[PDB]
């Protein structure tokens, strides 16, 4: 998805995977 937001694209998975935990609704 473009070699720009790459890093974000790679941290978001961790953010979602963090938030899921906190509120998995």
Image (cartoon, rainbow, N blue to C red):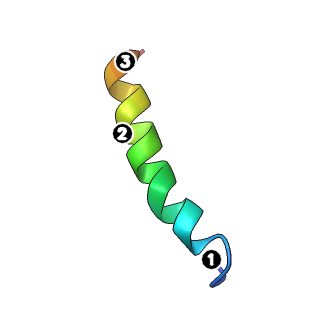
Look at the image and tell me whether residue 24 can be seen.
no
For the point 37% across and 18% down, which residue is it?
Answer: 22
For the point 57% across and 73% down, which residue is it?
Answer: 6
Compare marks 3 and 2 and give the one earlier in the sequence: 2
Tell which tag, 2 or 1, sits nearer the viewer: 2
Around disc 1, counting alpha carbons within 10 Å, would you say few (fewer than 14), some (14 to 19), or many (20 or more)? few
Compare marks 2 and 1 and give the one earlier in the sequence: 1
5 on left or right of 17: right
Determine the CA span between mark 2 and mark 1: 20 Å
- Residue lying at the far left of the rendered structure: 21
Mark 3 vs 1: CB contact within 8 A: no
Q: Locate residue 3, reporting x and y percent.
A: 62, 84
- The answer to which quarter of the image holds residue 5 is bottom right
Tell me, for residue 17, which label it has, or none.
Answer: 2
18 over 24 or under it: above or below? below
- Residue lying at the far bottom of the rendered structure: 3
Around disc 2, counting alpha carbons within 10 Å, would you say few (fewer than 14), some (14 to 19), or many (20 or more)? few
Quadrant assignment for the N terminus: bottom right
Determine the CA span between mark 3 and mark 1: 28 Å
Mark 2 vs 1: CB contact within 8 A: no
Q: Locate residue 13, reporting x and y percent.
A: 43, 51
Mark 3 vs 2: CB contact within 8 A: no
Q: Which residue lies under the disc numbered 1? A: 1
Q: Locate residue 11, reporting x and y percent.
A: 47, 56
2 over 5 or under it: above or below? below
For the point 50% across and 50% down, which residue is it?
Answer: 12
For the point 36% across and 39% down, which residue is it?
Answer: 17
- Mark 3 lies on a secondary structure that is helix
Count up the numbered dots.
3
Q: Which residue lies under the disc numbered 3? A: 22
6 on left or right of 13: right
């Amino acid at each position: 998805g473009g070699k720009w937001s790459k890093s974000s694209v790679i941290g978001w998975p961790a953010v979602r995977e963090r938030m899921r935990r906190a509120e998995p609704a």
